[PDB]
Image (cartoon, rainbow, N blue to C red):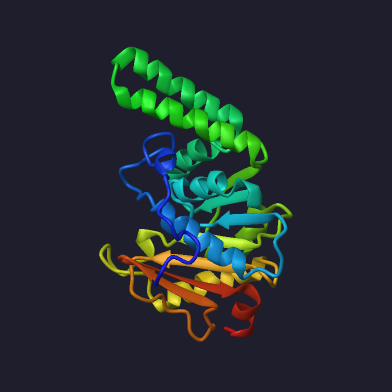
Amino acid sequence: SAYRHAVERMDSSDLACGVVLHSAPGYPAFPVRLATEIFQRALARLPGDGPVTLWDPCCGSGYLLTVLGLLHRRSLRQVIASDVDPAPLELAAKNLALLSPAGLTARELERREQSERFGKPSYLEAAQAARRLRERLTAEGGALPCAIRTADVFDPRALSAVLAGSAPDVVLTDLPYGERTHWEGQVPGQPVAGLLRSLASALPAHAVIAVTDRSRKIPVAPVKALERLKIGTRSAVMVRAADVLEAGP
């Protein structure tokens, strides 16, 4: 596949994992360029272009959702994060804190304090990145409403509490490594199918569900794929919520 939206390689350095946004040893970053490509492909499959509610129900460290929240602030009404275990969620919460000017100010201050203490140039590189992100966030809509809760995405009855009355237009998630057959591989068909059915039970009919994995092709049949892409070692697939429901059990 070719980049349709992220056509020219951007300066995504301010959003790099471990600069302003928070890194973890146990969770991967996600490439910014691919994140924005997938998100823009999903937006292109929505009926209209009003403000979008975006949900990541396997949010991990929250890096992915936070990249999208900042980068695509102008296109977003709110973001929702959820995942099954407490460990990732502590870090996801730190990342989501960056979706307000106050959170970015706090991170910038932390980096400036680290500069004074340690003297490493990178801390000041990070403080300036946080300042720039805050300035863009302020100009592009201000604080982005966000919520984060624990929930098992495979349990459809858990979902209404995560949504708290919101109707997500886009789900975008990087599949958790524990759902893979093994660490090297990919999530198999039955788990993917169950994930999609669970989500579609909670979403409005028009919602676009976009999932990505380390694989050549993510199995969704008998659901019809709206669209697929392959970039590097990663693939993505998008489906419509209404179509998932039409496929049956």
Q: Residue at x 46, y 75 (%)?
A: 228
Q: Position of residue 1 (x, y in %)?
A: 39, 72
Q: Position of residue 110 (x, y in %)?
A: 44, 21
Residue 69 vs 205, above or below: the answer is: above
User: In which quadrant is the C terminus drawn?
Assistant: bottom right
Taking the view exactly as shown, the residue that stands out farthest to the left is: 184
Residue 85 vs 203, above or below: the answer is: above
The picture quadrant where one finds residue 138 is: top right
Q: Relative to residue 238, is residue 1 drawn left or right?
A: left
Q: Position of residue 193 (x, y in %)?
A: 49, 76
- Whether residue 59 is visible to the viewer of this picture, yes or no, is yes
Q: Residue at x 48, y 61 (%)?
A: 37
Residue 109 vs 163, above or below: the answer is: above
Q: Position of residue 169 (x, y in %)?
A: 66, 62
Of residue 157 and residue 128, the one placed in the foreground of this image is: 128
Taking the view exactly as shown, the residue that stands out farthest to the top is: 116
- Whether residue 78 is visible to the viewer of this picture, yes or no, is no
Q: How many marks?
A: 0
Of residue 208 and residue 59, the one placed in the foreground of this image is: 208
Of residue 116 and residue 176, the one placed in the foreground of this image is: 116
Q: Relative to residue 83, is residue 49 drawn left or right?
A: right
Residue 227 vs 76, above or below: the answer is: below
Q: Residue at x 44, y 27 (%)?
A: 128
Q: Residue at x 48, y 42 (%)?
A: 92
